[PDB]
Length: 276
Length: 99
Length: 13
Image (tube, rainbow over all chains, first blue to last red; front, top):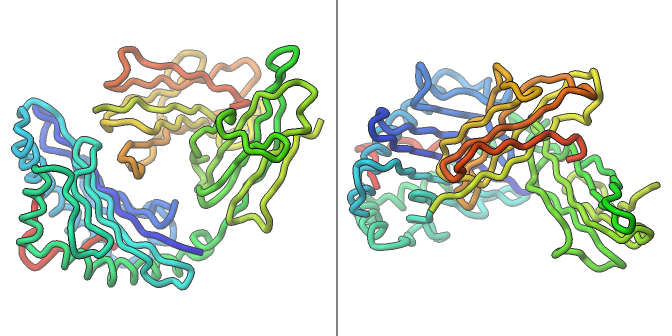
């Protein structure tokens, strides 16, 4: 169906321990395909998905030049933000940037993204119009003014509507056997007595791609949102993801509970019960 | 200002005694990015543990997967040891094959 | 493919 490409930049200062580290990673949907790390013995852009390996040496050198120049500029930016906030030269700080493009099931540009954070708090964002900025505070307004003066948004728009979309479509074709394949969850329900009159029902979803999934428990057809323990979706390490949802139920009432699974890889939404 | 990591310890495949598998420690929801993660076998740190490249979620918090090959038995105890600036003491999370 | 470098220099924050 729908698809996205995202780059994630993390720049981390560390006073007394060298220059700020810059890390860039690229994803198509829930698949990482590239990395760069300024701390590596020989910093270079590296493949992280098999379908990107076919790209020529000019691709890899272009990426490396981009990430190397960004490394330098992010170090300047970290110094700038430390100043904007009147911060001591003694603390470690982090700039993060996420950007990229979304496609619909056509797939044409649905929307572009470009957002930054400082120390884990939203700092500045490109608006959906790809023309204007939202600044979080007076410090970010300084960043806004110099991006407005340098016509940054104009460059962002040209990239997000052009090359971002073009290369995403290219990756989606080159990696179609995985990127355009949804693996449904493998599901089952476990039962764990906790006491004489309560037991845990745990609904498992395993081996699914992409990570987007809904697991819900119902009692008599009514969702148990407040009583459902829901873990964060977690990677298996083989491209696939895992999740569970659990409810503590009165013993003997197990059959009044149904687990419901929604995933794009499923022919139909699933309804599961405990099978003694 | 700072966020404490969520920690899950689990296996890639359904755990079967005497069968080679992958032991995972997924840390997520944390900020800042500096984190220490060890995998333990019977209380002792496992050598050659690998991790995924630093990335982050929509709320800006970081996530990482630490992983190594392992062969589960009935008697071998596995755990994750996590340290972070938010934690005053390292947090040990035991592997439960039903989790 | 990441954002290519502009003609001049990258604009810092």
